[PDB]
Amino acid sequence: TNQKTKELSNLIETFAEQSRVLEKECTKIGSKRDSKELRYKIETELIPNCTSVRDKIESNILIHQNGKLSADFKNLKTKYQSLQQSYNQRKSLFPLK
């Protein structure tokens, strides 16, 4: 409703996308597309931006005030964590060469 909290959803809205992205880039990790540029883009562009997107959401106290939104990012950062883990492992099992 509020413009301030509205701006938060904009960050979350991206996180939500970045979330699917991580799982997207993570799904290809060690699978054909497996390329240094990918893992690099992932850790140097995706995750860094996804998590950075969190700090932006977490920075907005409205995230702690708004119960609904509070869960929004929480679900993203949460699901995002699973992605990094599922991929981080795969990346260790599917080395490039």
Image: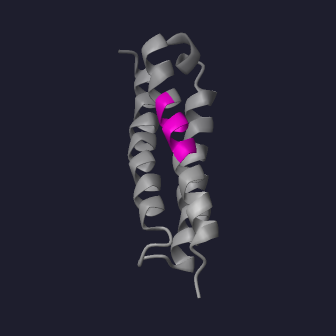
Q: Magenta span has 40?
A: no
From the viewer's side, name the closer residue of 41 and 55. Answer: 41
Whether residue 77 appears in magenta in the rendering, the answer is: yes
Residue 63 at x, y = what percent? 54, 20
Please report the residue visible at 60 percent of the width from the left and 45 percent of the height from the top: 52
Residue 60: name its quadrant. Answer: top right
Identify the residue shown where x is 38% and y is 37%: 13
Q: Main secondary structure of the magenta part?
A: helix
Residue 9's place in the image compared with 51, above or below, is above
**Quadrant (top left/top right/bottom left/bottom right) for the C terminus:** bottom right
Q: Is residue 9 left or right of residue 37?
A: left
Magenta region:
75-82
Given residues 14 and 47, the one toward you in this image is: 47
Q: How is the image coloured?
A: one colour
- Measured as percent of width and height from the top left, residue 72 is found at 44, 26
Considering every residue shown, the one lying at the far front of the view is: 93
Question: Could you say where residue 90 lies in the image, as x and y percent from the top left?
Answer: 56, 64
Taking the spot 46% from the left edge, 42% from the top edge, the residue there is 15
Say above or below: 25 vs 38.
above
Quadrant of the image containing the N terminus: top left
Q: Position of residue 16 (x, y in %)?
A: 40, 40
